[PDB]
Each structure stands twice: as structure tokens, then as C-alpha cells.
Image 1 (cartoon, one colour):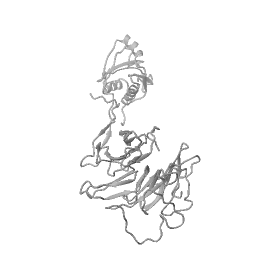
Image 2 (tube, chains in turn red, cyan; image 1 turned 120 degrees about the vertical axis):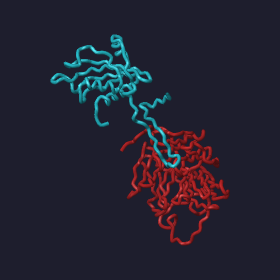
Image 3 (spheres, chains in turn brown, yellow; image 1 turned 45 degrees about the vertical axis):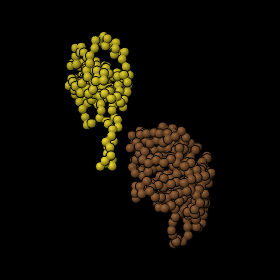
Image 4 (cartoon, chains in turn cyan, yellow; image 1 turned 45 degrees about the horizontal axis):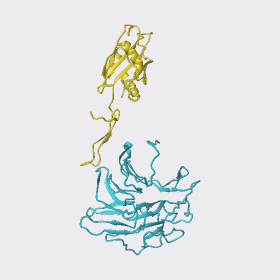
Length: 281
Length: 161
């Protein structure tokens, strides 16, 4: 109905909308992190996290705080509200894409764009988890259905899905029948970002811009570094699923699922946003 | 004191959710208007005219329409804004008049605002139960100035806010 406010500027790699607020917190690769609590058409703060670019934005999970990543390689959580830094560690050799907050003993998970992501105890000091299975440059890192199960999208042309543990990664199982992750007609490839057969999914599509998950589900909706943004369901795994998402002119940087909407929104580069179904598609 | 230039106020304000509270009210104000602020203020007419013309021309709003004669109506408006009409000529605000009324006021943070409004005026089958008089508003910024013309426009009549 109305586009309340609109100025075109910002060169934007990472993004998030406030699930609680009508904020948008926006990550530019201008090196900028911004929180604007978008409501009153006003920015609360604006820090260009470092000289270098900024790729990442993720939620802490609480109410109004950012966990942020730059080419600093640092995980910062700073509360806009409390304008202060919660606990601090820098980052490996690339930026931080996703974060989750937990609390047996007020306990923490950090998801990263490089190498490993490490999950840390500052209370009764022990190890909840270690994640290796990333390399460099994560476009879109994701919590899964199980929130603390996860997927990652890479500029290392892989995807990682990991299994975690309370004493590092492992799963025990023995009942299933076939798999959709990989087990009948169609299915898409493994990539390499880690080295355990959970599934490293192939992020080659000239590299993957975005990865997006299906909560209980393993369908992914993707942005890809190909015109082809190729959709695959690992809750099916169709053939002509070797779908290349097509503009008219080039690209499909991203195409995304809206939690509520059984739809795909695509956006591209001929000057465009392209409109897609996904209810009958 | 405290300059904040967020005009007409309407500036976001916070009551916070910070303790037995998960939310609260963040509010921007509205309800902050002019008609009140300015006080009446005065001038020599020749100089005035000269000045009238001279001033920040840039705003005007029209008077036309009401519920009253500009006797009672004018008085009401005057009191409402707390502002001045500088001088009469007896020509007659009665039989018609076919009077243009010059008004001046000075405020609390000191802007002087000038008006010439020229107005028809009530009287049987003669003229005035509208106006179609033009209210010429001069205040330095047009933005407040016109806004003032409005504000007065709000002021002008009496109806469901």
C-alpha cells in the first residue's frame, strides 16, 4: 500500500529485519553496520565496524541487540539499547554470519565465515562445541529448523550443514528408509567446506550468495553467484530443479523464502526485483 | 531553552521498557502548536506598510468560511492566538465593513509576524458569512509561516478536532 520512506543509497551485502521490531538492521560492505530502528525513520547508531568491508549481520536472539561481523573478524555483540558490548572475542580469518544465544549456565554459540566457529563456556568453563567446516567468506549463514543445527553458504563454493554436540559434533541414529538429502530421483551435490558426511552441499554455482533454510525441513532457498539460482528441495530433490533462475538479462543474486509466504522473492541486476510463486510456483 | 530544531516539536521521546516492562512507550509528540506562543505586538502605520511589503512575503492562507461575524469571530481568533491587530480606521466593521485588518504579533523566542488580511464581513444581504479574504502571512521561514497560516486556519473556526 505505501512505501513509507525511500532513498537509494548503501551498497548492501548483509541484511536483517527485526522479528520483534520494525527495525531493519543493515550491513553494508561499505564497512558499515547500521541499526536503524526503522520505525521512526531514524537510525539509532551507525558504526562502520572497520575500514574494511562488513558482510554480516545476525541476531543474538533476545529483543534488540546486534551481533556483528566485519572484515575485522570479530564477533561483537553490542546491544543498541544498552549501547554496550556484551562479551567479546575477535574472529578468525573472515567475518561472523550467524549467532545464537543459549543458557544452561548463561552459555554461548558463535557462527563464523572462516574455518571454524567456536562455542564457548565463561561460567563452569568447559567445551560445548567446536565447528570446523568453513573456510573463508560466508555469504549467508543460517540456523536450521533445529536452531542449533545449521547451514552455511560460501565463496569457497561449498555449503556446510553441521552437527554440533555438547562436547563437539556427533549424532547417534539407525532407523530411516531412504534419504532426500540424498537417496532417490534427482538430488544436488556435496560441496566441501568441512569434512564429515553430515552433508556438505555444493556451493558451487559460481559460489553461493545466500542459503536459506526450511525450519523442520531441509529445502533451501538460495541466492547464488550464478544467473542460475538453482533451487533444490532436499525434502524432495527434483530434476528440473536444475533450474536456473533466470532473469531476462543476467543474474539472480538472491531469491528468498518469506517465513510466512510460501513464495519466492527474487531480485536481480537488470534494474530489478522479480516476482516468483512457490505455492504452485 | 534547549534548542532542538525539530519543529512543531514532534520529536521522539522515550519511556522505556527497561524494568518490569518488556516494552513501554516511545512516542513522538504531536500536540505542540503555535497559536498560543505568539503574543501581540505593535507598529507606525506608514512604516508598517512599507514594512509589510518589505517583510518575508512568502506565506498566505485564506480566510473564507465560519460560524459567526468577524466581530465575535475576530475577537475569538485574536484571543485564541493571543495576537495583535494593529489599528482601525472607522470604515466600519459594521455596515459591512470593507476593512483589511492589519495584524502583528511577537513571540516568546522573538519572531515578529505580519498580516494583512483583507475580509468581506457579515450583514444581511450585504457582505460576509464566508470571507474570501486572504490571509497574508509573513513569517521568516515559509515553513513555519505558512504553517502558521494553517494554524490559524485551524484556529479560525470552531469544530471536532
